[PDB]
Amino acid sequence: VTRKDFDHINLEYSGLEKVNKAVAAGNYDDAAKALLAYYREKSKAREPDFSNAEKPADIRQPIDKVTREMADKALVHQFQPHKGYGYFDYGKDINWQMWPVKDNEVRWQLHRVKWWQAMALVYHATGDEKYAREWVYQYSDWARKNPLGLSQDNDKFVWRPLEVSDRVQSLPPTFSLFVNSPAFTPAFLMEFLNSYHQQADYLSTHYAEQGNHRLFEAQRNLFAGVSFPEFKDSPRWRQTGISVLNTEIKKQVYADGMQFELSPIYHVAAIDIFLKAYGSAKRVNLEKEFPQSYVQTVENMIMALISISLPDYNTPMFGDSWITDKNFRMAQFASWARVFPANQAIKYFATDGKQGKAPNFLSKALSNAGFYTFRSGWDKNATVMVLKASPPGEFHAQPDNGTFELFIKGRNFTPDAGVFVYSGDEAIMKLRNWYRQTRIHSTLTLDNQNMVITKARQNKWETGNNLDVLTYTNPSYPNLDHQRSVLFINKKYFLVIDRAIGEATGNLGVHWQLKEDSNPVFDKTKNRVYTTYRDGNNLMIQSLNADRTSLNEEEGKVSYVYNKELKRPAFVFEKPKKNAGTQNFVSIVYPYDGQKAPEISIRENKGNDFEKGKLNLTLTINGKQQLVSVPLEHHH
Ligand SMILES: [Ca+2]
Ligand SMILES: [Ca+2]
C-alpha cells in the first residue's frame, strides 16, 4: 500500500483522523487498516441504500431461486448478462472479452456485473464466506483486466457511460454488504476505492448532453458522492449531479407539478428519478446542497399525482399509460413519506387511508398540464372524474383533448382506450394508430377526424361546494374550435356542454365509451344510454339537445395492460353543422342507484345564452327540478 493509494481520499474528512496520522507518519498499511475500520464502522451504523435502483433489492427478503442461482453460478464463473439468453461459462481465469453470442448487448450488459449484488445478498443472508472471497477475487480480476484505456474496443463496452453509471450505483450497497468479510483485505479496500474513484470521476467528465441517459447518469454521479463523501472529489460530483437534475426538473415539469410528457405513468417514473436523488442525500445529511425550488417541485409532483389518483390507486390511462399494482404504488408512497415525513396526504396514500389525513382539497385543476379532477372525496366510494385538456405532448400523448375517466362507487365507468402497443412494423403501427384516434375518446369530432393538436386554452376554472365548473377551448381543426364545459353538480353528476365554433361544416359527433362489462342499453327514442349492472351502481349518459340529434354505436376497445385488449361499448351523439352558425350539445352524465334509469328533461330559462357565456337551465329529474345558473367563461 503506497502513499499514492490515498491521493484521492480526503484525509481531513471527519472520522479519518487515525488514517491521516498514519499516512503523514509513513505507515500506509496501518493507514489502510484504519480506513477499513472506519468503513466497517460506517457500514454497521447505517443500512445499505438500494433505493436508487430501478428495482431496489430488499436486504431482509428471503433469497428467491434466481438470486440463489445467480450467486452460485458466479462461483464457477458462469454469468447471465442478458435476459434473452442463459448463462455462459467465461472460463476459470475469467475472459471479460468473450463474445459468446453476436450481439453487442451481451458484452455491454456483462459489465453491469449484475450478479455481484446477488452474491452480496446471498452472503448477507447465509453468512457463508465463500461468496465474499469470490467477489473480492472478481472485483480485483475485473479492475486489473479492464483498465480505462486498455484498447479501443474494450473501452467501448466496459467504459461506456451508461454501464459505468450502473456500476457506480450498484457498488456502494454491494460494498456495504461485503466490507466486514475477512476476505475484504485493507489492500483490496484501496484497490476498490481507487477503481471506484476513477469510474465516478470518468462519469463526471463523460455524462450525456442529451436525452434519457443524461438524467440517469447525473443522478448516479450524485449517488457516488453521497455514498463515498470521503473522496476529495465527492462534493464536485454531487454538485454536478444536482446541477443537471435541477436544470432538467425546471425544463421537464410544469409549475402545477405535472411532468411534460402528459402521461401519468411517465410522471410517476420521473418522480422516482428526481426524488431518489434527493432521498439518498438526505439519509446522510447532504440535502442542503439541493436548492429549495427542487425540493418543492418534487413534493408538488407527488401532490399532482395524488390529485389525478382514482380510488383504486390507478391513474387515468391517458396517452401511453396503463393500470398499475396498488401494493407497489403504496410502497412507492411509503418511501416518499420517508422523504416528506410532515406530509399527511402522502402518509394517507402510503397507508391506504389508515394513517395521515386526506388531501387538503377536493376538485383541483392542474392548469399547466391541463389535468382537471372533479371529486366528491378521497374515500373508496367517492365519485371522481379526471379530465385532460392539455397543451401538446410528444410520443406518449394523443389527440384526446376532452377525454375523461369517471370512477363511481368502486367502478371505473369510462376507462380510456389506452395504449395496447408501442411502435413497430406497419401492422403493429396500425394497431397503435387505432388507439390514438380522437373518435374513440370522450370528446367532439368533425367527420370523425382526429383533432390536429391538443392546445387547450382554459376559459374558466372554479371550484365550489355543490358546483365545480371547467370551460376550455381547443383549436381542434383549422376552421373549427371545440369549446367544452363540464359542471360537477351536487358532488354527484355532470352536465357537459360542447360547442363547435367556426366556419367548417360536416358531421359533429360527441363520443362516449364505457367499461367492458357494463352491457348498456342504447335508447334512441330518448337519446340516452345506461348501464345494466346487477349490483345497482349504474350510469346514464343522455343527450339533452332540443334539435334533431342521433344516437349510434361504434367499435370500442380498452387495453388495461400491454398487448391485451377487450371489446367494450362506445357510442356517439351526432348532428349536422350545415352553415357557419355555432352548434351546441348539452349532455348529462348521471350516476344512479338501482335498476331503473331516471327520467331527465331540461328547460332553457330566460338569461340562457351560450353565445355570451351564460348558462341558465332547469333540469327535471324523476319529477324534481334542479336550477343551474352559471357563467361559462371568465375574464370577458
Ligand atoms: Ca450515455
Ligand atoms: Ca387514449
Image (spheres, rainbow, N blue to C red):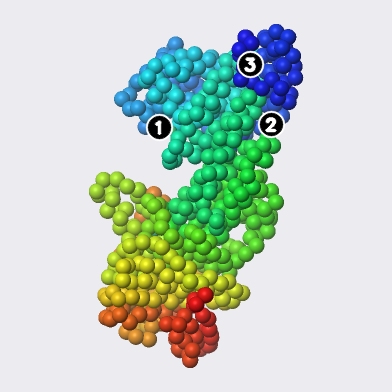
Q: Does label 1 or label 3 sit earlier along the sequence? A: 3
Give the position of the N terminus as an image quadrant. Answer: top right
Q: Given the current orientation, which residue lies at the most extreme top position?
A: 26
Q: Number of callouts in the render?
A: 3
**Tag 3 residue:** 6
Give the CA separation, mark 3 to mark 2.
24 Å
- As drawn, 510 above or below 292: below
Amino acid type at circle 3 is Phe
Disc 1/disc 3 C-alpha distance (Å): 39 Å
SS at circle 1: loop
Label 1 CB less than 8 angstroms from ligand 1: no
User: Between marks 2 and 1, how big is the CA–CA gap?
Assistant: 33 Å
Q: Nearer the viewer, residue 306 or 73?
A: 306
Classify 10 Å Cα crowding around label 2: few (below 14), some (14-19), many (20 and above): few
Name the mark nearer the viewer: 1 or 3: 3
Image x and y of residue 114, in percent: 49, 28
Residue receiving disc 1: 83
Q: Which mark is residue 171?
A: none
Ligand 1 positioned in quadrant: top left
Residue 571 percent location from the top left of the image: 34, 71
Query: Which residue was labeled with disc 2?
Result: 46
Residue 23 in the image, given as x and y percentages of width and height: 70, 12
Task: Name the secondary structure under disc 2.
Answer: loop
